[PDB]
Image (cartoon, rainbow over all chains, first blue to last red; front, top):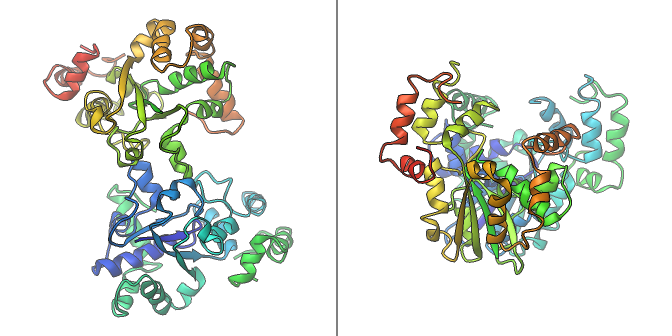
Length: 241
Length: 241
């Protein structure tokens, strides 16, 4: 049975794949390759010319930023049982983009707001816009995975209660007991994460506030935000009003 | 029926895909996307979450640098009819790497010579070494494409006689008459190529001598070159002694 950790880029997917790994592993993990090993990232596999077998007879966890309707996923149409769809406040994704990427912002925000996401950003591909992505993995999901049940979780909820919010993913994914959760929440940390990334870069190895600028932007973001356009729909729904 | 233009990176694959396109197109092509359209590059498709259907009922041309044994190619096991395997003097691939990438060289050459290719180069993935790549697409080809016939062509031969050397690919690929060949050879040029690349970068759009350093390197390259190790085998065979 095939299981996706699906997410728009920068929705906190690394952080989540960290936790799911060190829970399944049991051991803490330091090396980032250790995470690609626990919850491999489809894009990465494909870049190597790997593609996981369709119809594994034991459970596999794969993570991706692809839209559920991407044709390369059609190989997994019948074998997909579960989807964990991880969601974040889109406003944060922008900051997360600058955070890693003031004239520079009041226009990327326009592109983002025109994009309704990161479509112009060459870093990722196949992700569509933020709402097209959420839809494909939630409400329109059976159009590309008809056997699948979905559990959505917000970055915002995982941060305010990491333990409980994780167990839900664990239990949903029927990965075992509620016991490992704390020690698994423990080794992944907005600090210990930053550290794990560091070691791995250094060894070589493969790796990885609004108005402070706005004023004029704000009136446009909030128009997108409260504006009967699928983005706003999904903002309304996952509490980003 | 599925057809590959297979090549080690920097074997002149863009140049060849240019020609095959403007022959099938008929029109000259300026824009690089125009080439991705004529002979799409599997890696690129996959980066978007596209994957061409297995068992097309009309002929498709796809280009790739993957080893023929990469698991993602297994979808094409039975539907592959033909392979054009494009080969270049490995020594040139090194220069081609520096050319786009003197302390800097006498060690990349060591890595290349230790690699027997570009395995350490993060630009490409899944290509294996130069001889593993050639083997997979030539002599060991039926291990991953059992219905396939193969025609090998050398960059070196395409440069000294572009017209005739192309017709052979055309005829082999049963793409039509010998007539378009010259006008198709014509629009692709070690100059007009450089120009096409330029326009496309500028518009935005997606795009792309030994001893002068050696002495000490030379004695190691030629040891690899005349040294009963599969590299030398394939050097012996395609005339790089």
